[PDB]
Image (cartoon, rainbow over the protein chains, first blue to last red):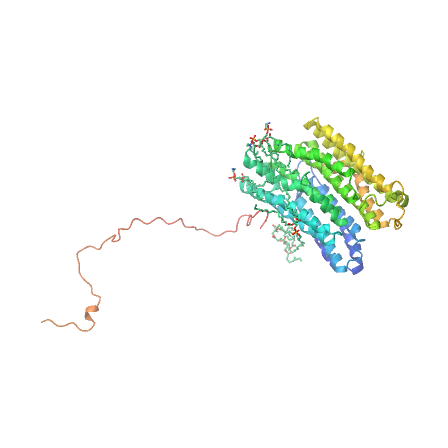
Length: 459
Length: 57
Ligand SMILES: CCCCCCCCCCCCCCCCCC(=O)OC[C@H](COP(=O)(O)OCCN)OC(=O)CCCCCCCCCCCCCCCCC
Ligand SMILES: CCCCCCCCCCCCCCCCCC(=O)OC[C@H](COP(=O)(O)OCCN)OC(=O)CCCCCCCCCCCCCCCCC
């Protein structure tokens, strides 16, 4: 992984040593080159994972998450450089540095062989994320959002640290390959119940699990646009990636310990989907949409079937591109009208025709139109959950109806009807904005041609 | 015929002939506890390093 870690680190001197007026050009160009080389991680084998060294490895689960991560950095630089245009040079460079450091921690997080190396980098991502939210967020609420983000994550992750060290003392190793062969079944005792919760709650909070999600509508809404993109696209998926890994050592206890969290997710997805119908803040609506989608990933991971694991991997990738696109679309309106209220600016299809096409495509992927990879992931999860219990099709079916309703409600409210008379500063869409949207949707639809590369290790 | 000893004479350490055998265990000591086994041999580098969590050295 050093062929990706070292180039990522070099983005920092590149940013600091660049000419003042070339910081965005230079960092964007070279971050795209790194993203291009990440395609070499697609050398996956049917039986064995691609094991680089004692520290790092990549299998079909981490590889797509790595490619998404490295793809997101140039998109975030494009999304940020407009609203940071009046920031002074040194603070711009520090903003880019936080983004680079977050990428460094993420790519090492997804390839860490040892769960305690995974833990340190998994917590490490908090620091740059907190700084981005609180320093460069726009509203007073960013300070409160940072505290909710920080202490929800740590309340869960500190018990995880105790559990992981306990496992290493008992097994002798936290190396993930070793745990595949030395894993022992978990006896059903009270002490193992709390080991199970310690190993899972930190990941549940990051998903987020319904009930433990209050940090997300604060953090995702108060962050700057780059903060929201990475928060929704990648950082929510650390929880899914962590759960997909750690459930290996929790069988068979997951059979019954899953029930309370499956109920929270199956009912929670309907609750959060309903909330979207009455949200007044466009960014807040998009944030609650993420909670509903990640409820499917939680359920898929907990029922532990080959189909649910393929579906979960696809959804995580599909949601990452879609939710990031929606935040970027919402941000482009915000940079014009300087409000997040959804009813403020209406009929934007009349004033911004091409941008209204991006809204439509973003909405259709969000409601999982076939054959998008959003639908492929959702379908595979619904199939596996039907086998877990036929009755689940009712909750899955209702959620798909509600999801269509709020996805198109967002489209209709903002893009259709009559334009707001007094809003007269809706200038034409910039080339930058149009390129930013198409760099989300084009890869998303291309993956429909070759879905296997985002179906994970069970494929 | 008695001659008074000179200054310093009576404070000399002298040697005495005796048939009483030298006591073997005048303190009546128990047998001493056995020392712990010595650690011996050549010092070799630690196997795979510190072995602390993920560190490879
Ligand atoms: C294992 C599973 C985990 C998953 C479940 C996690 C559940 C969620 C946990 C939430 C933690 C608490 C809430 C954190 C959100 C941020 C708190 C906050 O912002 O409250 C604001 C409140 C107002 O006061 P203040 O902000 O100071 O006024 C302005 C001056 N700055 O500020 C205050 O009044 C002071 C707030 C102090 C609390 C700080 C947070 C500490 C949390 C750990 C509690 C420690 C408990 C130890 C007690 C042991 C003995 C019983
Ligand atoms: C809103 C806050 C958000 C945070 C949420 C935090 C969730 C934490 C949940 C922790 C609960 C963990 C369970 C601890 C109880 C002990 C578990 C246990 O060991 O019981 C074993 C037994 C298994 O039963 P059985 O399947 O029959 O055994 C195998 C034979 N077939 O036990 C069983 O019968 C299995 C059933 C256990 C689950 C009970 C479910 C209760 C009803 C659903 C509640 C949903 C969650 C409610 C959260 C509200 C919080 C205010």
